[PDB]
Amino acid sequence: ESGALPKEAVVQIRLTKKGMIEEKKVTVQELRELYLSGEYTIEIDTPDGYQTIGKWFDKGVLSMVRVATATYETVCAFNHMIQLADNTWVQACELDVGVDIQTAAGIQPVMLVEDTSDAECYDFEVMHPNHRYYGDGIVSHASGK
């Protein structure tokens, strides 16, 4: 289990450097480059508000699935953990149509689940006890414990 995402996933981040603060929507590809630049402290938007990213993880190639609600769609690793309405965690590939999940717009039911092609994936640590963040607008578990 992880929070692993491919390069094209979109997250909302906040960059800080020496009093400068910037809020940006970025792909996970761009986030990796910003992380490896070493120039910033990076926070990510979450249902707990912005939280600092700690460690980064290159996860290699994983099996992938597409999960969509009415408002949001993510392509994520098969074992990318997504938060249910009851706040428990489930692997993306084990979601079924109708399941209520947490999103940036509140609870929404899953409308579509589809296996897709393998992809290079990435994960990271979120420095908050809930260890969660918005990935493509869907509440995801960072480092996927």
Image: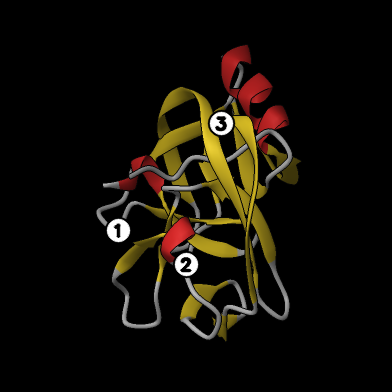
| Residue 107: assigned label | none
Q: Amino acid at mark 2?
A: Pro
Residue at left offset 66%, top offset 24%: 34
Residue 10 shown left or right of residue 122 in the figure: right
Q: Relative to 133, does residue 63 appear above or below in the rendering?
A: above
Name the quadrant containing residue 20: top right
Nearer to us: label 1 or label 3: 3
Q: Relative to 28, does residue 35 appear above or below in the rendering?
A: above
| Residue 130: assigned label | 1
Q: Earlier in the sequence, mark 2 or mark 3?
A: 2
User: In the picture, which quadrant includes the N terminus?
Assistant: top left
Q: Which residue is label 2 attached to?
A: 47
Mark 3, other Cα within 10 Å: few <14 / some 14–19 / many ≥20: many
C-alpha span from label 2 to label 3: 23 Å
Residue at left offset 73%, top offset 76%: 71
Residue at left offset 67%, top offset 20%: 33
User: Who is closer to the viewer here, 123 or 53?
Assistant: 123
Q: In the rendered structure, are the residues bearing label 1 and label 2 in contact, judged by CB atoms less than 8 Å apart?
A: yes
Q: Which residue is label 3 attached to?
A: 121
Residue 19 in view (yes/no): no
Q: Amino acid at mark 3?
A: Cys
Secondary structure of the residue carrying tag 3 is strand
Residue 97 shown left or right of residue 51 in the figure: right
Going by the picture, which residue comes out furthest to the top? 37
Indicate the position of residue 84 as horizontal and vertical percent values: 39, 75
Nearer to us: label 2 or label 3: 3
Indicate the position of residue 65 as horizontal and vertical percent values: 59, 52
Residue at left offset 63%, top offset 45%: 13
Secondary structure of the residue carrying tag 2 is loop
C-alpha span from label 1 to label 2: 9 Å
Q: Earlier in the sequence, mark 1 or mark 3?
A: 3
